[PDB]
Image 1 (cartoon, helix red, strand yellow):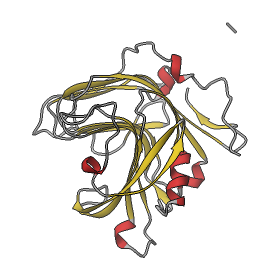
Image 2: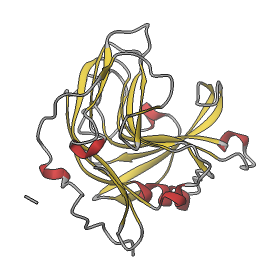
Image 3: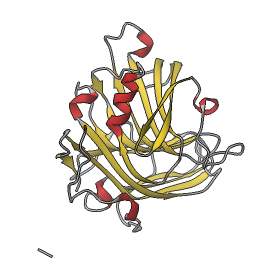
Image 4: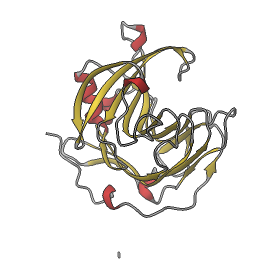
Length: 272
């Protein structure tokens, strides 16, 4: 019932395999979202100074769909590099309509990012009117891929022994089943200081390094499983998270776009 966007500005992720160059490399924590010149996007880096060298490099507004980045980590303590929509303007997910991210990247192989790692979509949302105070703040992940670890292949999807929490259900978006997990974080760091909050994970059962993520598919079907996001979406960004290890992530494409149900573009980046 939701029409797949056909717009010619959409880059086909499957053939988006040209290495990109240039842009500014950041080696330090950004301290929240930092807006990028000539772009609707913001980036964030979390680079704990008690660990080794990390970086994030934005490839700019004019190539690789406009949100494309490279990241590196060398024995980090939970590196997070992310880039995408920053919102935080008191709107629920439904306000943004059908959200999509076309992606294609290379990364280092199995066991190059520690015991835990995440690649995919990430953000937060606020639900202050929830009667359960634990559910008033939500940290969320749509996990397309990871690096596996010493025990588990990177071709095998992670489970609750990595994430923690409880399996809520499963659903299908973009040609794979996703196992859905809810986890409670008790007095943990958050965008709101040290507190109790919930986490939502969609774990792609069949990991991939390219394709399109129908982000709204997740938001909607989380809601069907009783996992509500509230009325103040914080952000929706493409993430690489590395618990430890020595590795890299290098996007040839990260392209966000939004469309109504007819499939017509509401937002996209970027004569013969």
